[PDB]
Image (cartoon, coloured by chain):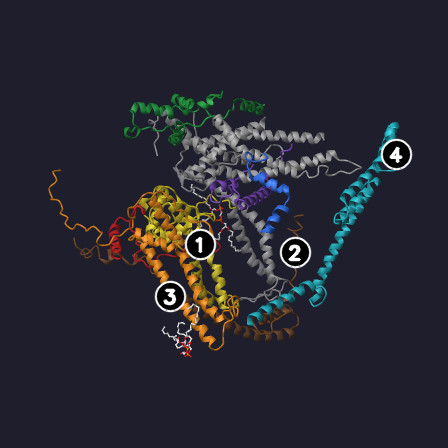
Chain colours: C brown, D purple, E cyan, F blue, H green, I orange, J red, K yellow
Amino acid sequence: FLFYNQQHKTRNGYFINHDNLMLASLEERKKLIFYFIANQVPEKLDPVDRVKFNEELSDNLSTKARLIGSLTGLIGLVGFPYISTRIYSRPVLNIGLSLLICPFLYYVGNQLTYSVWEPKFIANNNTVCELSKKYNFTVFDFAQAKKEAHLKALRTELV
Amino acid sequence: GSCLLIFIQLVFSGIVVLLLDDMLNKGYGLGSGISLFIATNI
Amino acid sequence: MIWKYLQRTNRGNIIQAGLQHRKFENLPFKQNFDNLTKAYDLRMWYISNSPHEAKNLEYVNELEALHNELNYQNSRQFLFRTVSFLLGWALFYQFYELPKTYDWQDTQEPKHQVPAYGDLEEGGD
Amino acid sequence: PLKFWWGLNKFETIQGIHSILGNAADLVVSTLSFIPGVQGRNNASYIENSIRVTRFRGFD
Amino acid sequence: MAIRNFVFKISNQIQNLAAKRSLAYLNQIDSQSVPSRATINMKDQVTQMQREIDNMANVIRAQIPDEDRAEFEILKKYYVTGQHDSLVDPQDVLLQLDRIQVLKNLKMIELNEEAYDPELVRLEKLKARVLLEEEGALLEYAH
Amino acid sequence: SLINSKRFGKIFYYFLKYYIYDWVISRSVKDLK
Amino acid sequence: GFETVVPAPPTRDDELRMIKATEEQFLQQPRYKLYMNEAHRIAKMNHGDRHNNIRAHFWSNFALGLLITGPIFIIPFGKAFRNLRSGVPYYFRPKYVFTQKNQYNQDRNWGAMKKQIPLWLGLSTAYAYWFTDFSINDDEWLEKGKVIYPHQTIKVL
Amino acid sequence: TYYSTNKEALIQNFEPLNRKFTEEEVEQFLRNEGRSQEEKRNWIYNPHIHGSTEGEWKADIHEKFDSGKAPWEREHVKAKILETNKAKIDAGEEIQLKPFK
Amino acid sequence: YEGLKYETPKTFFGRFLNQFNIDAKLDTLSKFYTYQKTIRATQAELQEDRKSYLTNSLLFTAVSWFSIYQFARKGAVLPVLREYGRYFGTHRLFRQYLHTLVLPLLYTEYALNQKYYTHMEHLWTVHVNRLNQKILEDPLYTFYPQELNVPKHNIIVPTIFRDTPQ
Amino acid sequence: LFDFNPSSIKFEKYPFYYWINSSQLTEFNQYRKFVIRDSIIYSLNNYII
Amino acid sequence: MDNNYHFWGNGDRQDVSLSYEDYYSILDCLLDEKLSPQGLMKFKNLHEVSMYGVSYVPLYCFPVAYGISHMLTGKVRRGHSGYRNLFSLMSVVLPFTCWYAYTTPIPRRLYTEIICSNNADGAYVRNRIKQQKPGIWRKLSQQLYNKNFRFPELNQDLTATEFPLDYVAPHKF
């Protein structure tokens, strides 16, 4: 809804829960748990591993999503004047139309590139597999990380 | 009730959810008053 | 609102249904079961709802004739369908590979086939 | 502010639109998998399917 | 040949049914002239719909201020036939609406604004805005 | 073969080819970045 | 399947507290609930309560089902008794008794009702069983038959 | 004022666990099925399955289960936590022992 | 035996090319596990199915050729194909004979390959797995002939009975 | 009617093919006195080589 | 969909499907001593659900048998007067429809728990069906492999070093 911000709900593996882990293999369960923990609770990792995971995520999901959203928003700006005539100009109306269109197209493109590339990044990335083997998180770690992520989202909403 | 099940779906227990559930209800109600106050002004 | 399509009963549910003229326009050039049934239904409905006794009695005679003819048509249908059913039944069991691999424990009662209480069934102690 | 279309995700129609777009993009990638450097889509992996079908599961 | 004859019998019945569906309203073959009425009924509905729209405009034409009527008419026309015609420019429709709005503001100036200098300023600006005979340099020198 | 090459490069807008390359190729290895 | 520590046999004060708890729990039984004094009584009573809860829901749904099965299914079903398959309007076919169907649509309406009321009740029962939830009383492993004693329910002093 | 006080308490006194659960903590969690609620468990000592001696085993069991002391409150567990996560100890990050509740 | 991995083909073209190795694979199995019950049963069933399908195809071909010849003697040629071919000008009679001889055989081969392709893939996968694990021992359900079996020792002498002291 | 249906094709030529005797593939949890049966099966499968 | 997905006698489309004939045959080759008290509980719940189900199946098939028997007599409905032919044809046809129903697998949570459980009871049941009911296990192994179940007892087991004990029907790898 309008009251709260929900851009984090369906991005960065926030939707992973125990149902994703019950049916997964041991290695796949480890990969999913590590991905959720690294995206949501980076404090559980060493700083070097945090930097490596951020670099691997940015060039694949985060910054790519930002760029795709920017391009899709630029698609909605073929003509910036939009409604405009010699007799009257509509600067405020055109600004409002841009603020209504470009954020929408940005959201659509960002959600698309997350819906396409995130599963492949989780399942077909060497850095994620190597760091998952390095850390080897358990189900208890995933439960604690889920609690911490929800509490951090609540705190961000509070502030 | 519904929020209790939703928050228990996330890793939580029935006792802990009630403390967390109350805060969200209080926060949402405060926003509703702020929206109601904004409507009266404009 | 809700009462318009929840409480206001439709017209068709109240008045008597009219004759479906679509089903009497293009009839096959045959005295088949369909045409005989249509004639029988027409005359039965007429005698059920007509104050005219002369036409009613004419239709009664014609209805008896139609009953006989429909009995003949139904006899043909019964013969063909039931003979086909019996032949298909026989052919199916002729080609079906009957499972003869069922358990035979029910036929065997070792305590009874060889009486376990032998020499004791007659009173002896 | 600018970010409320993200909050619009709760409607099942928007989720269906996103699913249609994602599946179309997956088809485009799969048809373009002959070019080196693109992984493509694998239907025999549990992780990919689980991420695809449970993205909007349990949304609140 | 038997298969072809059976196929042609089916085709003949299908074509007779198709011509009956698309031409039942012309003839009175059907009892009580039912289907014809249906098509006539359709026309009535269609006519009513269009009339309904027009009547709505009449209502709006009687409740808006007298100064707005022309504007509404323009919009009304663009809702009826202007949009469906590809040779009509929405840019020019918007320009005409802007010109009418400028004229309305100019008439509003004549409602005893009682502003000594702003009267001349706004009159010159509106004269040069709708591209009248008055030059922009004329008001530029006037300022 | 010849027709497919002409239609693929001419009918489709140049921005879509830019969009396809940008969207498929990762940020780090992208030429334009 | 471990075991818990067995406390020593209670002293007179503990026995008196147990008696007080049992009699207080005895006082709580409504007089219109006729459950005899037995080990399983409390358990049975709990079961009964849950059962009653389910019952209420069921009947509500049943009533609701009737409403929802009124105009959606049964009335359109009754639209099928207007004419026969030959196009002739519905007329009475008597089985043994040649009843006089003098009233307007007595034959058609009575046949429609005979084939609609059972259909109405059947669809309503199907709706009630489909939509009501029996989860509160369902016990797959039958773990809820354990004996609960009255002094274990109430804490005294 | 309850909402304001609870919000302040949550914001001030909430930190992520900042560490991976140790092997001992996970083993204790897996053995928490042996904990009994509303009635103490009768701990019986079998030397062929528990090892050690009866006194030492019973002392360890009392420490682990009956005393209610958490796994992160054990000295060897704390040493393991401070050893296995020394990389996070460096660069000025302090490890949180007890998860927030 | 040195660690090579056998992967079942996934492409349609790969599967179509691979279905011609089926019989070959069986021969290899018949030389590795000759007395394995599953291998022997597969051999027997494949042989009997080949014989039955070949006999049925030959009977169909004989009936078709007999019918075509007998009806063509009276000028009744079934209008199934074009009259005088397209490239070599062969006649409809000759092409009907050729088709009624060949197409039943192709269908028989296709059906035989379809029945045993997955079964032979499983057998070969098991063979390759137990070679990769360096298991050259005979499989479980291997029943050797008489000369390779161990005779059962008949002479079993019960121990001397003695009274229990307790 | 409209989904995957298991096939009924089997080995219908090899004698006593479905008289399966105990092995590590069957976990030896059968009827106790079936050991005799196993012997018989063994002997039978040595008769057909 | 339904509000009673928790019920053990219920099931969804992708649960293990066993016909009543298969269920009774499977029961014919098991021992209660070899099952843990939880497995016995599963079998007892399945027993009560299945006794009610076998009682009810002819009621399910009665409309179809009635229609087929009516269509065999002809296009005349002699209610109360064609009862003799109708019910002779019924006593013939209703067994056939019940044959089709009882040979039709139906999915159940108890079916998918008894067969596909990963504890010792599931392995015992799977191996017992594999050895004593080769045909039933052939069909059941095909069904389980199609449902992404990976057990050693399946004929379609690509990780095994021992040859399959039956004919492996064609399937998509």
Please, is residue I85 above or below residue D52 in the view?
Answer: below
The residue carrying mark 1 is I16
Q: Which of label 4 and label 1 is nearer to you?
A: 1
The reply to whether residue A11 is in sight is no
Amino acid type of the residue that numbered disc 1 sits on in the rendered structure? Phe
Separation of residues labelled 1 and 3 (CA atoms): 25 Å
Q: Which of label 1 and label 3 is nearer to you?
A: 1
Amino acid type of the residue that numbered disc 2 sits on in the rendered structure? Asn
Question: Is the residue under label 2 in contact with that under label 1 (CB below 8 Å)?
Answer: no
Is there one chain holding both mark 1 and mark 3?
Answer: yes
Residue E110, labelled with which disc?
4
Tell whether I165 sits left or right of K109: left
Question: Is the residue under label 1 in contact with that under label 4 (CB below 8 Å)?
Answer: no
Residue C10, labelled with which disc?
2
Image location (x, y in percent) of residue I160: 11, 44
Separation of residues labelled 4 and 1 (CA atoms): 90 Å
The residue carrying mark 3 is I55
The reply to whether residue G15 is in sight is yes
Image location (x, y in percent) of residue E116: 88, 27
Please, is residue I10 above or below residue I90 in the view?
Answer: above
Tell whether G93 sits left or right of C84: right
Image location (x, y in percent) of residue C30: 58, 74
Tell whether E114 sits left or right of G150: right
Tell whether E143 sits left or right of J14: right
Q: Quadrant of residue G7?
A: top left
Separation of residues labelled 3 and 2 (CA atoms): 70 Å
Amino acid type of the residue that numbered disc 3 sits on in the rendered structure? Thr
Q: Secondary structure at mark 3?
A: helix
Question: Is the residue under label 2 in contact with that under label 4 (CB below 8 Å)?
Answer: no
Q: What chain letter is assigned to the residue under label 2?
A: C
